Amino acid sequence: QALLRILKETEFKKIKVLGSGAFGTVYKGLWIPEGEKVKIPVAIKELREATSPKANKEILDEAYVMASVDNPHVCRLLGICLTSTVQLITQLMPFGCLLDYVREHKDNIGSQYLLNWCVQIAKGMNYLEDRRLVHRDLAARNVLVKTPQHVKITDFGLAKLLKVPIKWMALESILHRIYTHQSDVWSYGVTVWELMTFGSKPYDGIPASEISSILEKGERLPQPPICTIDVYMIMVKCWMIDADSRPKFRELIIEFSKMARDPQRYLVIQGDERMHLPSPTDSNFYRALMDEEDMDDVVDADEYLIP
Ligand SMILES: O=C(Nc1cccc(Oc2ccc(Nc3ncnc4ccn(CCOCCO)c34)cc2Cl)c1)NC1CCCCC1
């Protein structure tokens, strides 16, 4: 019944690799809770750096807060396994990361989807601010697609305890290692900019070492071709030097929700009205994650977790 489930090595299996980078490797696999006779599709993140049994209580305390998050726009930590390594277990998000998604589907993404994703991300970020949890690493690479209609924030927590994403960071975080919910708003603006450019790399060609001086001179990310000046001004406001003058996530939810009621007024996308995204049944990203032989008689995590 534990909110943070403590999993034995025997209670999960890594089936295939999903991704690999800085902090470690993510696998698609199955959660098979002991004696419960049920198989749950999960992702498994195994951290690169070794762990000691001493820091374990500090990791568990941090992990408890991550396991406590319950919002439809935030991924919940389902379980943890601490041995020589730290392994984290979460619900498999069967469409992958949003950064990749928008790059892939740039020809079938309408203004309605883009604006709805902005709303969902702000709602998730507002929920973390209610839990007094600064994300520190919001970016489109850390948002996951549950269905084309529904995205979720991931990769928050353990950050201060365990490469620097300079181009997403607020100026005060770069200069003084100040992180707050208002620095998260700055990263949210870069995130929205990534979505609206269908996954462009921010400040392409500018080296990370020069970013602080460019921001001090007043330079910012340019207006995405699809964005009206109403939408671009929201982004610009997220990057004000004065962190207290930036929008709050609560205010962002309101503004983007208004835009989402009349989407073609705020984004100009050629052929907008005719754009459709492949369903779970019609998707080959989805069917590639799920048509494996070992992904046979499974139960979705949201279902299993009905108390
Ligand atoms: O890790 C966290 N916190 C944290 C917070 C919550 C959960 C959580 O667990 C996971 C997070 C992400 C993923 N990945 C995926 N999950 C689901 N479906 C897919 C599909 C493709 N992927 C792969 C692409 O994922 C993109 C996101 O990386 C997926 C896997 C797990 Cl288990 C870790 N903080 C770190 C802070 C810095 C130091 C190290 C800890």
Image (cartoon, helix red, strand yellow):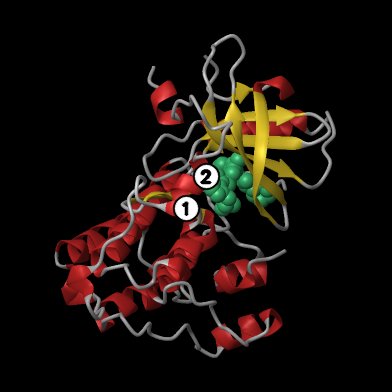
Return the residue nearer the eye: 305 or 185: 305
Element under disc 2: helix
Q: CA distance from mark 1 to mark 2?
A: 6 Å
What is the x, y in percent for residue 231? 29, 75
8 to 302, vertically: above or below: above
| Amino acid on which disc 1 is placed | Phe
Give the quadrant of residue 74.
top left
Element under disc 1: helix
Q: Is residue 28 left or right of residue 118?
A: right
51 to 298, vertically: above or below: below
User: Which residue is rendered at x = 53% and y = 56% of the image?
Assistant: 142
User: Which residue is rendered at x = 54% and y = 70% of the image?
Assistant: 170
Q: Is residue 126 visible?
A: yes
Return the residue nearer the eye: 30 or 254: 30
Residue closest to the far front: 293
Circle 1 sits on which residue?
A: 285
- The quadrant of the image that shows the C terminus is top left
What is the x, y in percent for residue 254? 23, 58
Give the quadrant of residue 230.
bottom left
Circle 2 residues within 10 Å: few <14, some 14–19, many ≥20? some
119 to 240, vertically: above or below: above
User: Which residue is rendered at x = 48% and y = 26% of the image?
Assistant: 298
* Mark linked to residue 289: 2
What is the x, y in percent for residue 105? 40, 67
Disc 1 to disc 2: CB gap under 8 Å: yes
Q: Is residue 279 left or right of residue 35?
A: left
| Amino acid on which disc 2 is placed | Leu
254 to 111, vertically: above or below: above
Q: Is residue 160 visible?
A: no
User: Which residue is rendered at x = 53% and y = 51% of the image?
Assistant: 134
Circle 1 residues within 10 Å: few <14, some 14–19, many ≥20? some
Mark 2 Cβ and ligand 1 under 8 Å apart: yes
